[PDB]
Amino acid sequence: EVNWSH
Amino acid sequence: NRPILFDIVSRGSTADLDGLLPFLLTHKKRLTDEEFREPSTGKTCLPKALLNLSNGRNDTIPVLLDIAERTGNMREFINSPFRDIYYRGQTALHIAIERRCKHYVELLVAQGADVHAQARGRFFQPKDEGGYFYFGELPLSLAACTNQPHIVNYLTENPHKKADMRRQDSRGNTVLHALVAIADNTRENTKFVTKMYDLLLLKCARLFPDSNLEAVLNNDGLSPLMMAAKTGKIGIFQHIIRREVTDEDTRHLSRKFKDWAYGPVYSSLYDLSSLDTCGEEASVLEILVYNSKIENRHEMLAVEPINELLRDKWRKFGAVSFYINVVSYLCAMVIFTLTAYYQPLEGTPPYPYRTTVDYLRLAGEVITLFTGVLFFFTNIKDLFMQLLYFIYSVLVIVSAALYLAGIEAYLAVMVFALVLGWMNALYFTRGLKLTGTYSIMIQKILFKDLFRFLLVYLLFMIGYASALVSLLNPDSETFSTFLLDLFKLTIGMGDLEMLSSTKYPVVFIILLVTYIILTFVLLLNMLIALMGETVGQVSKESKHIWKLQWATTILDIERSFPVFLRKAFRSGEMVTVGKSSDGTPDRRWCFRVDEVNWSH
Ligand SMILES: CC(C)CCC[C@@H](C)[C@H]1CC[C@H]2[C@@H]3CC=C4C[C@@H](OC(=O)CCC(=O)O)CC[C@]4(C)[C@H]3CC[C@]12C
Image (cartoon, rainbow over the protein chains, first blue to last red):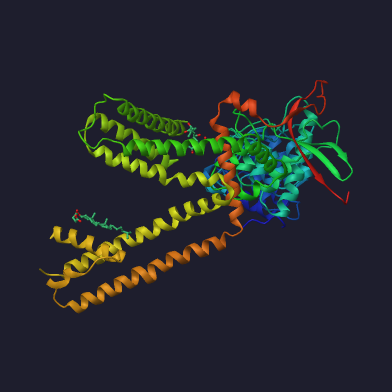
């Protein structure tokens, strides 16, 4: 997955 | 000694390294020897040490650098790249930047780390091309794409080495291209994407006032704005189309200026140089309207200058040409209908002409042939550089050719052309608003759902009718006759008198009963249901589809005209918005919009 808040 | 070295570095213990320097000196073995390096990839000691560290402090890196300097292999060791398909190109600096360790980035650049090294391994490729993370294939682009302002700032302005913002990888994309390539419509992503994009743009303009950073184009030939439009990224496209710069030094590159204000009325002119072109280059509007499979194709068009530009173009010249075209097409079809109607039945084609009425028919024929050849040429030019119209033109020309050759068959195909000639007249209602949405919906349902339904019905019908024919006992001719009879019965007219030769008539009656039931009750009803639900699902989409259809017709009309005529009709006023750095005037095309605000 892709997470821009971590 | 490779396993021992790998274990030592992985552990992170400083003590174990003692003695390596004299060992290498005595054996004169470099740290880049095949034995020391891992055969699988090529990973050297530095990337392994950087990969596994604690709270950003490995504590072994300086010792490794000192040892490599003692040997005298720093140039080939500190930037030794990986091999193999997955991670080809990656260097130590890429790792250091990926791990959010400014300290190590500085320590690496200070010693001569290649700052422009390209990491084009299959791991770093676009998602559609079998990869995980695409970032521009550069350290600078990597830091810009991982939301690290400090790294970008230090890297760009460093005494030892500077990675210039205007730099292109193998694909040609620059840092702005990558920063648009990783953008997503999420608020969190866009919030930093826009900020970093603007920061980097201002820095590049500041350093180099002469050149423009968005002027650069990749191998594909697009720019960040055109690429954002093509890739369906509203978040950055809307922020680049309305970019306004308050700083006087960097105001030249702004895109939306204030013109004047009177009370609640505010009037600002946007810039549309790149946005709208007259054939000089590719335009954002053409790309966004004509390309297929765009994520937010409909939402993207709802921007302050775009919609008003379409409106103004529509008023200025869109409406007139549309009505002219539709009227001319209808008249041409009427002429074609008359020509076909007055085709002399007597004799054989071609028919000699020796009277004025013959010359009237000939005039109609030449008009029809001219129309067909014109449509054919337009379609062929489109293909070289409208499928139904292509069929119409090809059929017309073939009919004319067979008329010249001499055969009755031409009339058939000629008539068929006439059918198609009117069959698509409905599609000219597209331009109209009230009926154009209905025409678009009819075309949409006709091609997608009706293809599936017809293909589903054909085999079922033919096989079931063949079964019924096989049931009867008194055989291609019998089947040919019975099929016509059966289809006529399907229409609701005729009589089933043929069943006299059949044994067990009861089962034939039952089978015909079930056939009728399926054809009328279930199959026909499902077709009814599908239309009702699709329109409900696209109830809001009606305005979207209508707006897209209106845009495409307008742009087709605009494209049709030659370049100089487009120059004549080009929309927008040349407005001197400022003086460039040298002091010369800008004189840049722009388009004006005014709003009303009672809270300002
Ligand atoms: C329901 C949808 C998806 C299927 C389309 C229906 C057609 C496949 C049916 C409807 C009427 C049928 C036609 C009725 C009459 C004739 C002429 C017949 O040959 C003759 O001329 C002898 C009979 C006569 O002259 O009337 C051959 C089949 C054909 C084309 C039949 C074949 C199949 C047709 C075109």
